[PDB]
Amino acid sequence: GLMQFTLPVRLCKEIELFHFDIGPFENMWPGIFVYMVHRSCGTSCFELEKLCRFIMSVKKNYRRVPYHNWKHAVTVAHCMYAILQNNHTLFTDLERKGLLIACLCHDLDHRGFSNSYLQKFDHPLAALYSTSTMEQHHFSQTVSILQLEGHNIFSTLSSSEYEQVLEIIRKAIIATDLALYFGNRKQLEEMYQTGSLNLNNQSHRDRVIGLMMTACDLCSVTKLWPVTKLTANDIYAEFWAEGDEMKKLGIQPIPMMDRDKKDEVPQGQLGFYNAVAIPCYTTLTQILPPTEPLLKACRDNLSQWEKVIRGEE
Ligand SMILES: Cc1ncc(C)n2nc(CNc3nc(-c4ccccc4)nn3C)nc12
Ligand SMILES: [Mg+2]
Ligand SMILES: [Zn+2]
């Protein structure tokens, strides 16, 4: 119980900032996550041995895909850690616990294909779950790992604390379905502006945690430009593989997924920052003012994509 994880000095200082990159050394990512659990939650939250066994099973159930991989899982958990550490007193003991686990688990067993591709291929998961197909699968795999021998990291909670934390994780993982983000952010925008937003209304917290999840999920756009730019190559490598698979089903993919329309990526990134990213971090900043560095970095990256279009980069 006296075994604190510590990080080298550059990582000790830089892990606290929103724009931190967890680096290319896979074997350090588990320790980075435990460090984050220990500071956002406590050395007491999880039995170390159960946590390590859960982490390694979560890792093993992420696939070797260009973007939706173990590195993405730990990156999304780190953004959540930053939001939680900059908003100390706004979140319950169970939310702290649940939300870093939700982020680590949110894309479990992803195959690098959209819900839309599963539906057109007619994948078994598309009959088991007609909306948020992959996200219901991700939650399902989380409950699976939680029920392996020696993996119940929540075993010290009561039946009802346990049920609340699995309910927090389910909603949080479901909210990572970008189709659901637009409606959720519109409602939050309206509630905040008409002054009805109430962080004691459970159905309001839910929406606020959904938006945090979208924020953490999209956080590649809040990094240093060279991280953002190199991550975008991973993002399009998945989309263009799905594009090819659409063409194999005899379907012209949307241009986002057509490797023949590589040229239009800079303009596609503008659409994406304007329609999804900027609105996301704006509304988050309105609700949680200390998350402003995320909006500031996103804006800086929009401006870098604008330079790419002007041939300045
Ligand atoms: C950075 C980032 N993080 C997360 C997600 C989910 N995405 N999704 C995109 C894709 N955005 C996008 N690309 C194109 C496009 C691309 C090439 C040609 C034509 C159009 N249009 N749009 C809207 N970028 C991101
Ligand atoms: Mg996902
Ligand atoms: Zn994700």
Image (cartoon, rainbow, N blue to C red):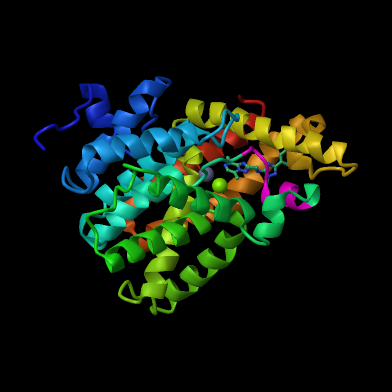
Residue at coordinates 82% horizontally, 30% vertically from top-left? Answer: 260
Residue at coordinates 60% horizontally, 50% vertically from top-left? Answer: 134
Which quarter of the image is occupied by the C terminus?
top right
Outermost residue, right side = 250
Residue 117 among magenta residues: yes
Please determine whether, in this image, residue 34 is positioned above or below residue 217. above
Residue at coordinates 32% horizontally, 57% vertically from top-left? Answer: 289
- Image coords of residue 262 (percent x, y): 75, 30
The count of marks equals 0
Please determine whether, in this image, residue 254 is positioned above or below residue 224. below
Outermost residue, left side = 2
Judge whether residue 175 can be spotted in this image. no
Please determine whether, in this image, residue 28 is positioned above or below residue 35. above
Residue at coordinates 56% horizontally, 37% vertically from top-left? Answer: 68
**Residue 309 shown left or right of residue 200 in the figure:** right
- Image coords of residue 224 (percent x, y): 44, 31
**80 or 232: nearer the eye?**
80
- Image coords of residue 198 (percent x, y): 34, 75
**279 or 32: nearer the eye?**
32
Q: Magenta segment range? A: 111-119
Identify the image quadrant of residue 308. Answer: top right
**Residue 144 shown left or right of residue 231 in the figure:** left
**155 or 277: nearer the eye?**
155
**86 or 72: nearer the eye?**
72
Residue 55 among magenta residues: no
Which quarter of the image is occupied by the N terminus?
top left
**Residue 191 shown left or right of residue 244 in the figure:** left
- Image coords of residue 199 (percent x, y): 32, 71
